[PDB]
Amino acid sequence: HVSAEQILRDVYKKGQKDILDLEELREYQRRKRTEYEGYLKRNRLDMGQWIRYAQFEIE
RNA sequence: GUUCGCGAAGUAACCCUUCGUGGACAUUUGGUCAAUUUGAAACAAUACAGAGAUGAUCAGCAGUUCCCCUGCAUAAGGAUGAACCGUUUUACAAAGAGAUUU
Ligand SMILES: [Mg+2]
Ligand SMILES: [Mg+2]
Image (cartoon, rainbow, N blue to C red; front, side):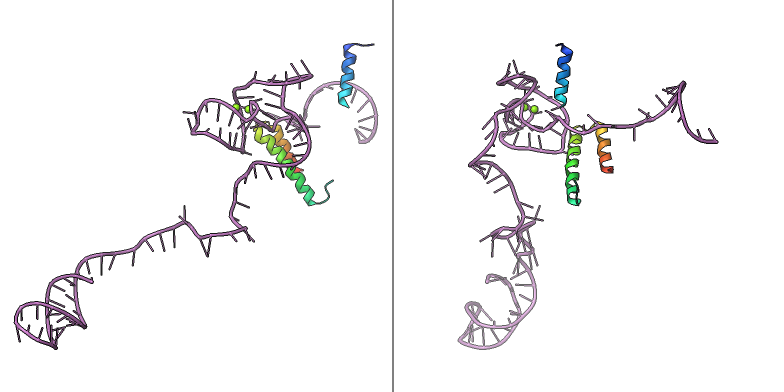
């Protein structure tokens, strides 16, 4: 039987569906810092991004 | 080189030369910069696509940015010039209940 809730359950179920040396580490680091410094040069605010980027440098 | 002397020598006679000699005049340019590759413009060609809020096709104005280009520009253009679309955990406590230990 067809109702709107069963349509939206169908839509929800539809849309729901190796560092080995130091140079690979430096590339991972350079790429991630370009990411975070980009999203912080654009939005100077948003302290949560600052805490995540600081936790990244802790890791 | 010029000029004022001061001596000698040639003719001298008060001039004119050769020569030595004291003074005067005139007195510090240019480089931030070496002459083809190795101290720094850049575009353009072959290949792929064929422009944002869309169900489709479009008008735009902004904003933020350690991106700028054309412009005489504080005007206006550059796809509304473009990038924007991701990753997301703790100022962490109170009352009650069920098991372990003392
Ligand atoms: Mg714009
Ligand atoms: Mg504009």
